[PDB]
Amino acid sequence: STGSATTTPIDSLDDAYITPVQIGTPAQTLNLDFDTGSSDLWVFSSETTASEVDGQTIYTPSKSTTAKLLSGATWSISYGDGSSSSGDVYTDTVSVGGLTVTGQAVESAKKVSSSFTEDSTIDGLLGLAFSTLNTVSPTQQKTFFDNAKASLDSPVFTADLGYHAPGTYNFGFIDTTAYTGSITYTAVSTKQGFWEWTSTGYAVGSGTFKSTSIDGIADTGTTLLYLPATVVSAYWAQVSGAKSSSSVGGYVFPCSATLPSFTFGVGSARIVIPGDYIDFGPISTGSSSCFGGIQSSAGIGINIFGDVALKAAFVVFNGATTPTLGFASK
Ligand SMILES: O=C(NC[C@H]1CCCO1)NC1CCCC1
Ligand SMILES: O=C(NC[C@H]1CCCO1)NC1CCCC1
Image 1 (tube, helix red, strand yellow):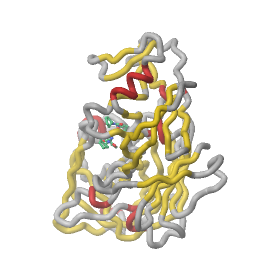
Image 2 (image 1 turned 135 degrees about the vertical axis):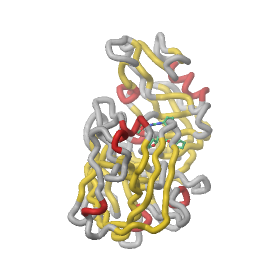
Image 3 (image 1 turned 90 degrees about the horizontal axis):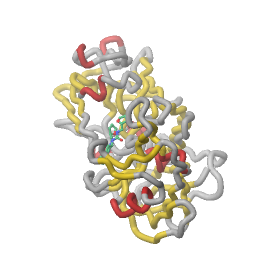
Image 4 (image 1 turned 45 degrees about the vertical axis):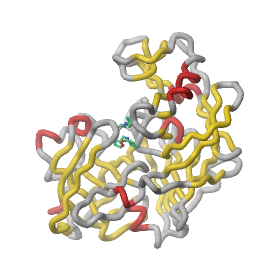
């Protein structure tokens, strides 16, 4: 089997991407955040504290004839941005882009933190990291991909995120028309539960490539590119007037600037992030200070190749017995 679904930016900045997901019978379609840095499929629901729902579409398990309460199971997750959610668990039928999993754990939120409430466009998360990170207790549950992968034509999914435009998540096949050149594959460590890999270096604009190992994860659920402070300083030094602002929380730059590209290495291959992809717009409405899309990882403990990086590539998440990542230009 295969599946293919369009993923759409939630706003004009590509702050996140939402993908429609069918849950239950009859289907209830929710727009989820496909997240390769976590492993829980959770949704706003009829069980979510009413004051914490503000415009999201909810899953109502009592209206799904295939929903079954997973007796005694609870979940609770906290993310690297400080957000969180928790609740109970159903199993139900879940379909993405025509690919169907029966008995998928659907984690129903009883509580969500304010950032989730305040974002009416994200109805929940669909985790695509390794199932070792799933938070369901006392019986850990499998991700949608883990449940589907034996049925897939090939045990892979691909992320093709758009810049200020829709893109595609495919399951079970590699669309050879969706990229240019070749896909370069690189080793993955699953020891922390992420799609963790080692970039071979970077360049800023037209500058020389610096060969240096940068261990990080491929995270569709992280918006920006988080790299070591040395690398980030080297980038922003090429933008006149850019500076790290403790009050704002990262590097900012004059909105009048033209940003240079940023290149990262995948083996001997090179992925070029155009400068425009690094502009996250005014820090507050009407400001001429703009927020940068490349930020230091020093305070996170791990480098993150988030959407800023991934959207410059066609990315293969190869879930073979020994997982690997693939990157192609597009
Ligand atoms: O939490 C992370 N990103 C943001 C969350 C919010 C909802 C989806 O993703 N990234 C983690 C990756 C490893 C360290 C932090
Ligand atoms: O990218 C991050 N959050 C993504 C937003 C979009 C929708 C959900 O939240 N958070 C990063 C902060 C420092 C590492 C994780």
